[PDB]
Amino acid sequence: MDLELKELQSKMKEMYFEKDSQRGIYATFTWLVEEVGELAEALLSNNLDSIQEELADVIAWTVSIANLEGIDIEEALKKKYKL
Amino acid sequence: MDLELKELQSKMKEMYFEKDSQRGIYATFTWLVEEVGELAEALLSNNLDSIQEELADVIAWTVSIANLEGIDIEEALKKKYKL
Ligand SMILES: [Li+]
Ligand SMILES: [Li+]
């Protein structure tokens, strides 16, 4: 029931890695930025529904980059932060 | 051992919410953007060590915004994505 980081990462890879691989790293980063912009819009509008959606999208595209780069996000977090 | 999203979020709130609250939502978003820029630099340099660090930092600041906005990131993800 409680989603693990490792499961988030592996499930996203199964869904999106083929497409992300095809487009390449810089275009995938450009999508991340597009979604960071949508998060900006959501915060500026103070629309919690939008904020909720764009937070999910920003995480999802950050995970995409982790998957393209072969980096475990859980261990990246634990290396840098006290977790 | 396997870090849950809910634990990531709650632990980050304990560490950083007071400081993030003090600075406010738009300055906190500005820090997120600063780290997205560092991720850009890391990708451009193809330095995996840097990429690993900045991915962690981008997630961490995205979680900061979720905490400031009172949004559960796990449920945000599950609402938008098949997880
Ligand atoms: Li979005
Ligand atoms: Li950073």
Image (cartoon, coloured by chain):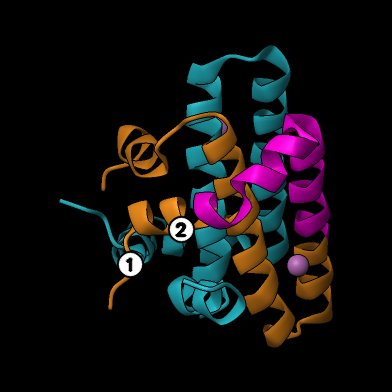
Chain colours: A cyan, B orange
On the image, the x and y values in percent for residue B72 come to 39, 37
Q: Residue A2, how many percent across, how many down?
A: 21, 53
Q: Which mark is in front, 1 or 2? A: 2
A1 or A81: nearer the viewer: A81
The disc label shown at residue A28, or none: none
Magenta stretch, residue numbers: B13-37
Q: Position of residue A66 (x, y in %)?
A: 54, 69
Tags 1 and 2 on a common chain? no
Using a 10 Å C-alpha cutoff, classify the residue at mark 1 as few (fewer than 14 neighbours), some (14 to 19) or many (20 or more): some
Q: Does residue B71 lie above or below B58 as drawn?
A: above
Chain designation of label 2: B
Res A5 seen here: yes
Instruction: Classify residue B51 by image quadrant.
Output: bottom right
Image quadrant where residue A81 sits: bottom right
Residue at horizontal 50 percent and vertical 77 percent from the top: A78
* Ligand number 1: quarter of image: top right
Amino acid marked by disc 1? Ser
Left or right of residue B26: residue B77? left
In this figure, which residue is indicated by the disc labeled 2?
B11
Name the residue rendered at 82%, 37% in the picture: B27
Q: Is residue A22 above or below residue B52?
A: above
* Magenta highlight on residue A71: no
| Crowd band around label 2 with a 10 angstrom C-alpha radius: few (<14), some (14–19), many (20+) | some
Q: Main secondary structure of the magenta part?
A: helix
Q: Is residue B38 left or right of residue B48?
A: right
Relative horizontal placement of residue B77, taking residue B37 as reference (left or right): left
**A55 vs A23, nearest the viewer:** A55
Horizontal and vertical percent position of residue B77: 38, 41
- Determine if the magenta segment contains residue B14: yes
Instruction: Name the residue carrying label 1.
Output: A10
Which residue is at a point 32% across and 61% down the rendered structure image? B4
For residue A83, above or below residue B37? below
